[PDB]
Amino acid sequence: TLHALLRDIPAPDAEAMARAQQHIDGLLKPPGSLGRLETLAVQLAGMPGLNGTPQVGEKAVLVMCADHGVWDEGVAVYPKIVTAIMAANMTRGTTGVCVLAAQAGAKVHVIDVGIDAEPIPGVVNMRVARGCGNIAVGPAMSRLQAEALLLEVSRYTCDLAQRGVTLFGVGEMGMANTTPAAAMVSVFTGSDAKEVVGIGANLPPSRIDNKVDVVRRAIAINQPNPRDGIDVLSKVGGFDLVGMTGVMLGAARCGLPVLLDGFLSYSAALAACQIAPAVRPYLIPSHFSAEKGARIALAHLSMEPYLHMAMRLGEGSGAALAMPIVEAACAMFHNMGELAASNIVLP
Amino acid sequence: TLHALLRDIPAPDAEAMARAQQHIDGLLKPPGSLGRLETLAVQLAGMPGLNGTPQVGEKAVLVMCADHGVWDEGVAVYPKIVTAIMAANMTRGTTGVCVLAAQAGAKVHVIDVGIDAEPIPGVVNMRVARGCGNIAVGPAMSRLQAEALLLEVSRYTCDLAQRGVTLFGVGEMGMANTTPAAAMVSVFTGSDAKEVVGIGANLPPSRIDNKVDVVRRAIAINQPNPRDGIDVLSKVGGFDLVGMTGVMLGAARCGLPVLLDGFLSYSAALAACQIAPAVRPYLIPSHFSAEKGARIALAHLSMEPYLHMAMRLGEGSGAALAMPIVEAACAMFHNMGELAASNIVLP
Ligand SMILES: O=C(O)c1ccc[n+]([C@@H]2O[C@H](COP(=O)([O-])O)[C@@H](O)[C@H]2O)c1
Ligand SMILES: O=C(O)c1ccc[n+]([C@@H]2O[C@H](COP(=O)([O-])O)[C@@H](O)[C@H]2O)c1
Ligand SMILES: Cc1ccc(O)cc1
Ligand SMILES: Cc1ccc(O)cc1
């Protein structure tokens, strides 16, 4: 049950983190000079599914795919079928995330959580429905549906741990999905929709105002409760957003790290942490999305991405791009020599 | 001759860059959505030693090692011998750069351009002298010495191209070397020394004022000419700084990319571009050094690092950390599918 899942997320291991910190301070560099590699290495040390030390075994990027009824409100530039096309492309290795995952030695799990098309062979099927409801006139989904999906995705994710996955990245694919992401960001952070509605997949400037109105209308009609994340997800989110949330809950329950991606992933992360604050220490940022609301969303999570790529593709592409960074923190930790063995004293 | 070298640096290939741009726009993503991977891929395309396309073959990080007489002015926290110790450690694979280079599949070339110790077996010997002169009372070196070293290093670097190196990173090791780097930054950018003098290798706050005075004194006594970079290097730089400059000149002459590292590398880069503006399109930033003057130096090069790690180790560690990013630009370019093959039309 979802209650049990949330309850049983482990706290970070303070003991391992102290040990990690002392090890790092003794490595063959001025103390603190590797900056955020150090802090990342200590963060990792504290994640119980890594067994007391910064390590990366196998890597999996989970790409949650779905369509949105709010497409019909004119907020997306690409035809609805692009979501289905791209999910099929994911099975052939031709996408941005696939290419960047291959570079990182990561496997990509393409999950259909609600594409409005025929099922795609070879894609993992968790489809709730053929696209979510149009958040401009009503809820994306029932609370039952959002709860079931979270629990489904969380279990899938934590099962990957038995196969030797120690690091996750989340991603999505869904035309129009920057609209619910913005709605959620607005609702969790209390920022006005005009501050958090971006151009998404190259929406023209003339169409922005409509998107802002649509976000405002979705929030007015649904009255999402900002202190109930599952309410927020179910009312003005999407199946993809819920899925990504589910990945974060599952990784956290497993005591393991998840790399965020971009703007969509930030919205999901806001929900994750609202639902369960104990998720927060397992989340690792990757890059700083070029999407307008990014700064606000990231500030509410108190996160500073490592990568400033002006990237806005989604798919988990940024998450993939950062996996080498996580690996570098571990290599630093395990493979550097020590000050003491060169007789270099702390000054 | 150094005149011939500088003269014969090639301009970037506009034709290849246009072709690269059109290819990238047709890949299976919204145009522009990979942001700085795109721009990096096009920058690469234009470097003539890469043969018309973004590619990475073998990778080499060149770590220029030397000692500085200005050590005697109380501007560094670690004993002078640390430079020699660490260069020896570089031969054993135990250093930050070694570990990060191994992660990136890069080879590290440890070059002694003036360590004040006995020569270290296994280190490439280009030593100009046993440490440079104390920039507080006089020049670091003669102009002849700075010219000879540049030319030596440039040739070494471009020779690595015959062995299949297509990407370089620069680094250094030298106690006290953040003092001349600051002096050079102050002189090239016209910023007051107080704005560009950092804590280096954990210099305590009580000792900062002395370091600022020392930079001011070095500039007052030497009167470096900001419009003659070789003058600036020879008077208030260091053998390590000159060497790194030489790596940038050699890579540019070869038509090939070099990754910058941190603050030291920025100072060298300022010199490189002053000496030869045609170097600039070959330089690629890695990370944003935690050193105080970083922002100013980087602004004068109009550069925005990809990585915000709060890193201040040097050694070429950041340069190594970014090589996977360069590789990702190429993988994007070569391995993504195309919009047209999925019948997705530009909207
Ligand atoms: O992750 C990001 O920051 C990002 C920012 C803008 C757009 N996207 C991607 O483009 C999509 C949605 O844009 P739109 O305009 O349809 O809302 C979708 O499939 C994405 O993952 C992704
Ligand atoms: O690259 C950097 O940004 C960086 C910033 C601060 C210090 N360092 C390193 O620490 C060294 C110099 O610091 P200091 O205080 O002796 O001038 C030297 O060997 C470095 O490469 C390097
Ligand atoms: C003490 C020290 C260690 C490494 C290094 O790169 C510089 C200084
Ligand atoms: C057109 C497009 C392509 C890829 C993608 O991830 C989103 C939209």
Image (tube, coloured by chain):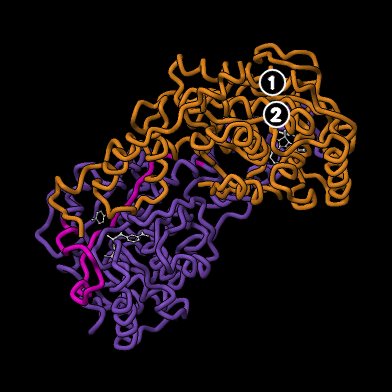
Chain colours: A purple, B orange
Q: Quadrant of the N terminus of chain A?
A: bottom left
Q: Which corner quadrant of the figure contains ligand 2? A: top right
Residue at 19% of width from left, 48% of height from top? Answer: B339
Describe the element under mark 2 as helix, strand or loop.
helix
Residue A197 is situated, as x and y percent measured from the top left of the image, at: 37, 72
Residue B261 is situated, as x and y percent measured from the top left of the image, at: 60, 37
In which image quadrant can residue A271 be found?
bottom left
Of B140 and A219, nearer the camera is: B140
- Label 1 resides on the chain identified as B
Residue at 66% of width from left, 50% of height from top? Answer: B296
Compared to residue A85, the image places residue B237 above or below, namely above
Asked if marks 2 and 1 touch (Cβ < 8 Å), the reply is: yes
Q: Which residue is mark 1?
A: B147
Residue at 40% of width from left, 79% of height from top? Answer: A193
Residue at 75% of width from left, 17% of height from top? Answer: B128
Compared to residue B167, the image places residue B76 above or below, namely below
Q: Is residue A179 left or right of residue B94?
A: left
- Label 2 resides on the chain identified as B
**Label 2: how many Cα within 10 Å (few below 14, some 14–19, many 20+):** many
Is residue A82 part of the magenta span, yes or no?
Answer: yes
Of B238 and B13, nearer the camera is: B13
Of B88 and B252, nearer the camera is: B252
Residue A236 is situated, as x and y percent measured from the top left of the image, at: 31, 77
Q: Which residue is mark 2?
A: B230
Specify the segment rendered in magenta: A55-84
Residue type for callout 2: Ile
* Callout 2: CB less than 8 Å from ligand 2: no
Describe the element under mark 1 as helix, strand or loop.
helix
In the rendered structure, which disc, 2 or 1, sits on the residue that comes first in sequence? Answer: 1
Could you tell me if residue A336 is visible in this image?
no
Residue type for callout 1: Glu
